[PDB]
Length: 143
Length: 143
Length: 143
Image (spheres, each protein chain N blue to C red):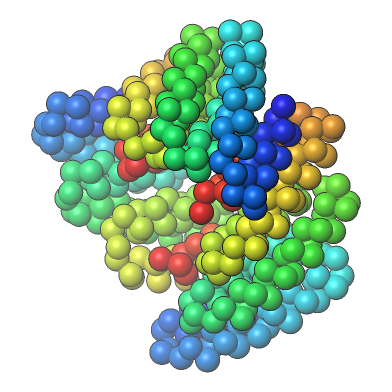
């Protein structure tokens, strides 16, 4: 499912044809909506990661903003689920995306989510993810 | 605890109040001494990492220094115990602190520790820790 | 002697003697020829990583090149073997040396290898590696 986007990315770099980046971003945007529906938040994680990395190469912040918005909604759902691990892995991707975009308010969103996920993990009693959340927190406050 | 620090960090981004960073640094410096005293080297790892990130923001090298001296003593104890994984994770944090602080001697300390941890890991199982030690070595020598 | 290279590397830092870097590079190049062809792609990964690190310190691109060419042939062999976890760990080290060397061509190599490994992993049905490959792919296209 990711193969066509990975090939198109290599093909756009070597041939210098940004229309191939745009084609792959279209494929990845279709897939990301299909996984946003259905509730496949683990796949949304990786599609949004790949979507944002290609969008960054193309120089078009629009697709970076779509990845942010979809990752933020997947985080809110995964936090309502009380999954915490999915929230952690979702925030990890959003951190890489926010680092690319440079939007300060995405980091603010992640600080609140991590604090809430720490509270769910504290009352659940999962110690290892409690530390993993604090570590991810120290990375967000950097920038 | 961690929750009060994470709340104060968020509260001091929202409210324009760096005193809340200072209050968090004070709590974490208390907890870090309490953890070093108890020998709680796994918590020493996470407190120092959070302390240094909150100290990097606000920009006070003092709390970076406390973090270096405590991590170093936690590393020496973990190396006495022969716990190659723990000293690996402890040096990993000290490398991030020392990169923030910029003191050459903190790197030199890490060079000698990793060589010793390589000897213990060589005579033990030649596991992934063996490559993880030499991998961490190459990162300490670089910058 | 792995330990000898670690010792010489520390020894060249505080004595400021780059002849010890060149001596460790000699020991590591002898060791890589022993390890390669015989196989042991895991040890090829370790010493090539150490070799290129102290070569970067020495300022000599030549040894960065042999670390690259040995890593690339290890990746091709591990890719022939079908060991997709091994090519992942090999490409991870090849990204660090490619960052040091600064040659655009090694990044092109890594993009093609990762696309292949995804295909082998997709037909093998490993799932977790497929995601880990895509995640590493987003790191390679950055730089």
